[PDB]
Amino acid sequence: GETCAIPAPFTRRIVGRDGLCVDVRNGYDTDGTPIQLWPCGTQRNQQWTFYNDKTIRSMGKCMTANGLNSGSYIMITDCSTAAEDATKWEVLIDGSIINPSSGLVMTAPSGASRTTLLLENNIHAASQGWTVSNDVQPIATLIVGYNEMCLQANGENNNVWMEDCDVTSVQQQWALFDDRTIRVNNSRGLCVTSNGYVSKDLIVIRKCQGLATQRWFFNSDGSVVNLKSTRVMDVKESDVSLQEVIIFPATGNPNQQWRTQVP
Amino acid sequence: IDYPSVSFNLAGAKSTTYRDFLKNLRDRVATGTYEVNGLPVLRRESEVQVKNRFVLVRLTNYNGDTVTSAVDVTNLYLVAFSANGNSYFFKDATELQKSNLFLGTTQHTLSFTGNYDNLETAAGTRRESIELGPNPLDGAITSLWYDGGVARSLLVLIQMVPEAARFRYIEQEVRRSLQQLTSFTPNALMLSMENNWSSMSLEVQLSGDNVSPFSGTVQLQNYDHTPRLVDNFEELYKITGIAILLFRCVATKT
Ligand SMILES: *[C@@H]1O[C@H](CO)[C@@H](O[C@@H]2O[C@H](CO)[C@@H](O)[C@H](O)[C@H]2NC(C)=O)[C@H](O)[C@H]1NC(C)=O
Ligand SMILES: OC[C@H]1O[C@@H](O)[C@H](O)[C@@H](O)[C@H]1O
Ligand SMILES: OC[C@H]1O[C@@H](O)[C@H](O)[C@@H](O)[C@H]1O
């Protein structure tokens, strides 16, 4: 065969809450400077390099977990002096920046600017969503489910059902945030929040709050499930007329398959 | 060699029939012990039996006529097709296929080979011009069974069958046409996403399973021809919707 060429150090950005990228406070490269949220842009204190050692360092200082227990904030520091088991990371496809050792993941307590990051317990919430890329701009696309219809949103705190795909309509336009939350392209302040964790629970459209019911991982199999439970977003009884999209265990049936068809 | 086959009858076929037809042609080559974030990595020639190397596809147009094409189980490429006891193979056509491809039919050899760069040339037209959909598929099918088989026609089936299973995006695209009985032409995106199958194939196996970030990038394109460099798995699938991966390398973080 042929093993894969050891990837070289590549630099990218990291977003994961309201569209904010993880930035180095003030931009100081000094050791100790905490890490938090800040509007994405052209700056060295926002670009991070990934190395084989699983160490993400910006400015040249490895990102290390100041502490080691639920609550310890994050910050940079000399890679040579900082603890090894505190400088390694893991960017899973679930958008969760986990730390092999501590087993904790990067968490954003609030989408408010300046919100200082801090490693917290991994409970699979929209607060632990993180997508690394040079494009902080979310994806705009529709979602075709059953009967070739598109999942359209209506008003706040109202169920979501499939309506005849209308590209021109904005009631069917969605924005796939990097924090792993699906918010209506129009008012990007409303995320597709579920209503529970038990199979057969409705799925409406309410404000975003890093809720665990607002975590969506686009399974490569075509299904759109939430991280917490294995429940999948589908159409009740495969009948779109019911106008009720809910969460149900992966059955592998058509009414559980989706597709983000670009703009 | 009784090679298997996946058939799709244009005869009043629905969109849900297209989704299944692709799922069959997919699983017929998805059989293997190598995955990555879900998407499988088609086997290679180094480990593919001569009795499992190929897979046939029977596409029947409105007039009942049916044309069968062989799709390599390794790269999902179109090696040859047959209509009315008449098989056709490309210029190169590795002698390995002919030896057991449509054995028992009048063999033929085209002056060109299988690949857009060539196909588009042997037709005086580019894919950005050739239309796809229900009717275009029918006419393309007829042009083969009747006129022997020329580039153009093939350019329609390739993006309407193999390339349709590789990228789910192209699927929902032909799924809207099949149902709405409408037609369309590949856009800057659809085209670019199908021009980097190999590239985006190594970026998935390189990063490894579960790893979202990509060491390199994929120069995709938007409808306005604007550059859209994808550097992560999620962002890639959400757009292209890849479902098949061409073996470009084996994992290392074992
Ligand atoms: C999705 O919604 C956004 C706004 O929420 C649309 O953005 C447009 O372009 C920029 C970027 O936001 C801004 O000028 C405005 O917000 C929007 N209007 C115009 C005229 O640009 C974006 O176009 C929407 N996506 C799609 C596919 O319609
Ligand atoms: O997040 C805190 C911010 O502080 C500012 O002073 C600086 O210009 C930004 O780059 C960022 O570091
Ligand atoms: O009919 C009961 C359920 O059956 C499942 O197969 C389907 O995925 C669910 O969405 C629901 O329809």
Image (tube, coloured by chain):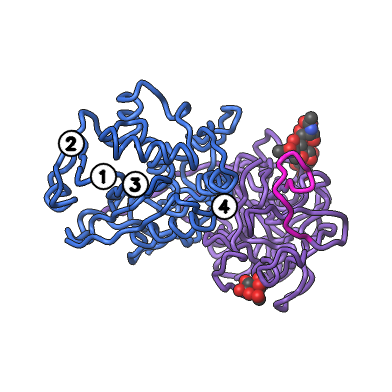
SS for callout 3: loop
Res A79 visible: no
Read off the residue under disc 3.
Answer: B65
Magenta-colored span = A160-173
Find the distance from the CA under tag 4 to the CA under tag 1. 41 Å
* Identity, as a three-letter code, of the amino acid under mark 4: Glu
In the picture, the disc for residue B234 is: 4
Identify the mark nearer the N-term, 4 or 2: 2
Q: Are marks 1 and 3 in contact (CB under 8 Å)?
A: yes
Is the CB atom of the residue marked by disc 4 within 8 angstroms of ligand 1's nearest atom?
Answer: no
Q: Which chain is purple?
A: A
**Separation (CA) of disc 4 from disc 3:** 41 Å
Toward the viewer: A202 or A103?
A202
> In front here: A197 or B113?
B113
Give the numbered dot on residue B92: 2
Furthest residue to the right?
A156
Are the residues under marks 4 and 2 on the same chain? yes
Is A171 magenta? The answer is yes
Choose the circle earlier in sequence order: 2 or 3: 3
Is B67 above or below relative to A249? above
- Indicate yes or no: mark 2 CB to ligand 1 under 8 Å: no
Among numbered discs 4 and 1, the one appearing first in the sequence: 1
Q: Is residue A39 left or right of residue B116?
A: right
* Contact between labelled residues 2 and 4, with CB atoms less than 8 Å apart: no
**Front of the two marks 2 and 3:** 3
- How crowded pointer 1 is (Cα within 10 Å; few <14, some 14-19, many 20+) is rated as many
Chain letter belonging to callout 3: B
Mark 1 — residue? B83
In the rendered image, residue B136 lying in the magenta stretch gets the answer no
Specify few, some or many for label 3: CA neighbours under 10 Å numbering under 14, 14-19, or 20 or more.
Answer: some
Residue type, label 1: Ala
